[PDB]
Amino acid sequence: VKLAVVVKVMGRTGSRGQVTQVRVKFLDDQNRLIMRNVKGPVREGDILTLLESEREARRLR
Amino acid sequence: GRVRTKTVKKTSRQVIEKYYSRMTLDFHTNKKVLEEVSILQSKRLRNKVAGFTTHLMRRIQRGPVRGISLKLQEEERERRMDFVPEKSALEVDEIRVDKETMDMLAFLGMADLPGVERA
Amino acid sequence: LALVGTMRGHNDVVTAIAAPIDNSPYIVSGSRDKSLLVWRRLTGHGHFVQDVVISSDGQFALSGSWDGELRLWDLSTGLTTRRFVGHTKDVISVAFSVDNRQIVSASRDNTIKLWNTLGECKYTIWVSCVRFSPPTIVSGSWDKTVKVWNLTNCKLRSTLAGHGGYVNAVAVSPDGSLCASGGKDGVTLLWDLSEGKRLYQLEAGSIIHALCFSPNRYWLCAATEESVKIWDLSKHVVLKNQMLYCTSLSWSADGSTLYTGYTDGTIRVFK
Amino acid sequence: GDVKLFNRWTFEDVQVSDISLNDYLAVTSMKHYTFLPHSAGRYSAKRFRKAQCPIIERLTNSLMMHGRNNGKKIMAVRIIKHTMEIIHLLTDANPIQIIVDAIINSGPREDATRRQAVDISPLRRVNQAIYLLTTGARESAFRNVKTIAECLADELINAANSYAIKKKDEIERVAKAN
RNA sequence: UGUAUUCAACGAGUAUAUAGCCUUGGCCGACAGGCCCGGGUAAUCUUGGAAUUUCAUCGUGAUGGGGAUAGAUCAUUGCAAUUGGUCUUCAACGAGGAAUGCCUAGUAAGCGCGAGUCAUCACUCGCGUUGACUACGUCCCUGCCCUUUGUACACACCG
RNA sequence: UUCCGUUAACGAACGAGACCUCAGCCUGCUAACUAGCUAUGCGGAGCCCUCCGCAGCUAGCUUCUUAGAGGGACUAUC
Ligand SMILES: [K+]
Ligand SMILES: [K+]
Ligand SMILES: [Mg+2]
Ligand SMILES: [Mg+2]
Ligand SMILES: [Mg+2]
Ligand SMILES: [Mg+2]
Ligand SMILES: [Mg+2]
Ligand SMILES: [Mg+2]
Ligand SMILES: [Mg+2]
């Protein structure tokens, strides 16, 4: 339950291109920058919730 | 898409090449001049040509382009002949001679040239 | 010269600002917004109106649209008092007569037309903006020349060919004794109507939309693209989207104010 | 204010208890709140355009199923009015609040695709919640004494123990195992 | 299912023989159908042009969903029986396995109308009505195109 | 294979684009008794006002329908 704001979008990835990989920062701690993936439609400036804040990602997944 | 057919590109280039004197920046003035300075059948082709000409006037008002000619700076000649200083850029004294060139001037050349230097 | 205020009630270019001779606060702005305004709105045309004027009595408004026609309007009711149709090419400018009974119009058809306000007799003789002499008529041409006509028989009086660029409009003295031009050359030519010879020049720099003569100060205000320039008749300028150009200048009857027609509707008053 | 839902519901009482699903729901009482969820506006033109659409419009448009029900938005908004009256009269609160609570408690957070688990878009979250609620109401309404409004009302209050919450539970269970 | 509001476009329509087409209106007939007054060789006349929407009986039951199938019966079309009216009969059918097709906006989906077919009998071509979910990405599959590369293929990998 | 450019290529033919039909906007124009809008007059009901129908060989108009010439958009401005 660590709400994160989408900071940049790294293009659609995946087999069908359904998942979209983005970089986010926490609203509780702005200075921490993580990479995650999101289904559905995502634009910059949005706020996204999660459950586990420790999972990492890769560039151009 | 919005890219321009070679016909409209060409005709815009020609109308600017031969009619840069009066044609202005507004699109509607460009089209009302095009309709009588040239015969274009399709009205929307004429609109495309007028808009393209306006875009190239925006391009050219900052500097010259690679497309048009005549009055070959943009509108007036005599750009570089005026770059003639009252004294030549080439000096004649203490003119850039080194050890091996000194040995050369000891060879067939004259070692007492006016521009000889000990550098 | 200082700022009075700003206007933002227009969505396109206002091309002509006309004020009644009687100095009454019923000025008419004719715009290429397909709409007019009264400081009442007019929309009877279907194209972009260019030139507007106000009758001598000050209770009517004459405006011509780029569709190629002209209309004289009942200002109070906002309805056309009369139409004027027969300019196949788009009209460019309008003006009244010395008695404000005949209407002179210049269009894109390389010709000028005189119309009766009520009569059915019409006569004809790219002609730019025209302004009748308060009785010859001056006009701009398509070859950097300014023509002066004769009202006695609709004949050409003389031609003035000293302009390096095209002539976008003409200026006449309030007493009908001067002529002035301007254009892309940036040098405004001033001549005398009587002899029709070149008097002198003033330096501005670029296109001047409207050249307005001061009725009282005997001055000349020009809407140069670089900076609006005002001369006194010492020939010396004794006025300031990435593109910024005016469209018209209008001298007030009082003489202490002036009104500008701009591009994005920012009508500005100076005093 | 001067704008109320069916001249009956006041929008200036409903908030969202989250800072991640605010802009996607048109519940703010400054704009985007309408008289009824029926409007002939275009929302599929550009991306993220349906976020500006009112939430009630989304709820009433997601009920025109199955193929024997589409093109009948009139029944949809009538049924939403009936279920709205049921909810307000029972719970003694603003039915907009119950709708928002049900939507905000019926959105799944994570899925698993490609099999790796990863999060869900908030617009997809609200869309999935609305689709789940409508399908659950349809399931509870088929071959039963209940009418549409009654099952819709029950699923709306139960989601503020319910079909939609159990569907989200199993989806999240499948997600969290990978 | 039964009452009661009611909003479209496209097109088509005569040989006048009493009258072959569109049919208005009046009368008769439960309905199907018949007689009379007639109009339109056409923006004139047909042309005055449904789902949906208040109200109620159902009440979760293979039930008033469904009407397959049958019998009795009347009349129209046709030279000669096709269809349409009335009642009775009331089958499978309670969202459909592997597979599988169409579609991104007034679109899909739902509901009718006209024309072609025609002595009589509606699938195809258009017309309009109600009207959304998601996506706005990709080459994962199915293909298409280009560049490099390999080839013992050239009927060209079904080689 | 649309263009800009690069260029042992230069200059050209098709295809694409261009073209044509229809729809989308016009209180601008053209003009409508085989199409309409409004007022009035008459008759219908509860002077006026709500109101339905009928004329006025021009009451006026084409905003509403028809069909024509035209315009509008060209990516121009940010
Ligand atoms: K049956
Ligand atoms: K009356
Ligand atoms: Mg019914
Ligand atoms: Mg209708
Ligand atoms: Mg049944
Ligand atoms: Mg049955
Ligand atoms: Mg067939
Ligand atoms: Mg009209
Ligand atoms: Mg156009």
Image (cartoon, coloured by chain):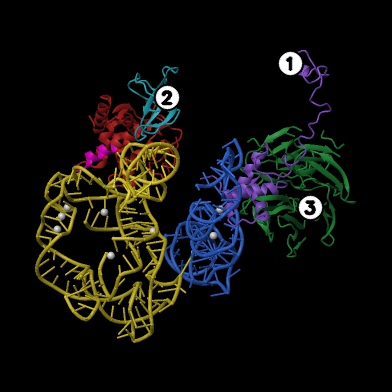
Chain colours: A cyan, B purple, C green, D red, E yellow, F blue
Q: Is mark 1 on a helix, strand or loop?
A: loop
From mark 2 to mark 1, how far is it between C-alphas?
Answer: 62 Å
Both labels 3 and 1 in a single chain: no
Residue D111 placement: quadrant: top left
Which amino acid does the dot numbered 1 rest on?
A: Asp
Taking depth in this image into account, of E119 and F11 the one nearest to the observer is: F11
Q: For mark 2, what is the residue?
A: A23
For residue C102, which numbered disc appears in the image? none
Which amino acid does the dot numbered 2 rest on?
A: Arg
Q: For mark 1, what is the residue?
A: B98
From mark 3 to mark 2, how far is it between C-alphas?
Answer: 67 Å
Residue F30 placement: quadrant: bottom right
**Residue at 58% across / 52% down in the picture?**
B45
Both labels 3 and 2 in a single chain: no
Label 3 environment density (alpha carbons within 10 Å; few <14, some 14–19, many ≥20): many
From mark 3 to mark 1, how far is it between C-alphas?
Answer: 75 Å
Task: Give coordinates of residue D161: x percent, y percent.
Answer: 22, 29
Q: Vertical placement of D124 versus B49: above or below?
A: above
Q: Is mark 3 on a helix, strand or loop?
A: strand
